[PDB]
Structure formats: structure tokens, C-alpha cells
């Protein structure tokens, strides 16, 4: 047994964020995420329009701060 796709990407996303308490900007997120999962973020594949929208859609496990600059920094929550 192993994680199902949506659970795999969620737990591994979460785990990178839990190590990286400084947060990771959305393109840096893609990088460090793919270092752990060996896959790119399934945003469009699951049907979210953007990397940000995928990260908006996990508020029970992950957290985000969209900066005034238009970047978004990603964080863990569980």
C-alpha cells in the first residue's frame, strides 16, 4: 500500500512545508515539492487553474500569504 494521488501530493506538500518553516514562494514550492514527490504540482491536472488556486484549496493542512508584490508564500498547518 501507498498514498492515493491526491493524498500523496497533499502529505508530501505538507511535509516539505513542515520542514521549510520560512515558507516557500509558489515557484520555489514547485521546486522543493518535486524534490520530495518526484512529480510536479498536479494543479491543472486536478483542475485548479493555477499553483496558487491548488494551494488555496488545502486550507485544513496548508496556509498561504499572498504578498502585495503579487507573489504568494506557502506554509504548513497540519
Image (cartoon, rainbow, N blue to C red):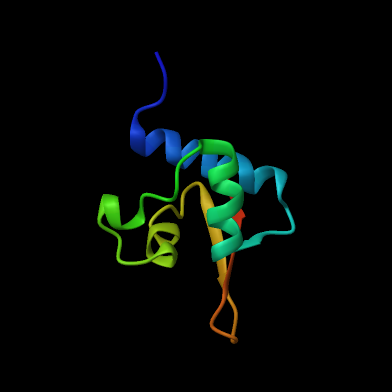
Q: Residue furthest top?
A: 1
Looking at the image, is 29 positioned above or below residue 6?
Answer: below
- Please name the residue shown 41% across and 25% down the image: 3
Find residue 40 and report its horizontal and vertical position in percent: 45, 48
On screen, residue 73 versus residue 11, left or right, reads right
Going by the picture, which residue comes out furthest to the right? Answer: 22
Q: Position of residue 53 (x, y in %)?
A: 38, 65
- From this viewpoint, which residue is outermost toward the left? 47
Q: Residue at x 44, y 40 (%)?
A: 9
Residue 32 locus on image (x, y percent): 61, 49
Rendered position, 7 above or below 42: above
Q: Where does the N terminus fall, quadrant-wise? A: top left
Q: Image quadrant for the C terminus?
A: top right
What is the x, y in percent for residue 42? 36, 49
Residue in the image at 28% along x and 51% along y: 45
- Relative to 69, say whether 48 is above or below: above
- Tally the marks: 0
The quarter holding residue 25 reads bottom right
Q: Residue at x 37, y 66 (%)?
A: 50
Q: Nearer the viewer, residue 63 or 13?
A: 13
Apparent side of residue 52 relative to residue 71 in the rendered image (left or right):
left
Q: Quadrant of residue 57?
A: bottom left
Camera-side residue: 67 or 59?
67
Amino acid at each position: 500500500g501507498h498514498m492515493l494521488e491526491a493524498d500523496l501530493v497533499s502529505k508530501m506538500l505538507r511535509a516539505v512545508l513542515q520542514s521549510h518553516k520560512n515558507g516557500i514562494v509558489l515557484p520555489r514550492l514547485q521546486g522543493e515539492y518535486r524534490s520530495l514527490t518526484g512529480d510536479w504540482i498536479p494543479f491543472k491536472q486536478l483542475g485548479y487553474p493555477t499553483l496558487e488556486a491548488y494551494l488555496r484549496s488545502v486550507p485544513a493542512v496548508v496556509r498561504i500569504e499572498a504578498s502585495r508584490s503579487g507573489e504568494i508564500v506557502c506554509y504548513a498547518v497540519a
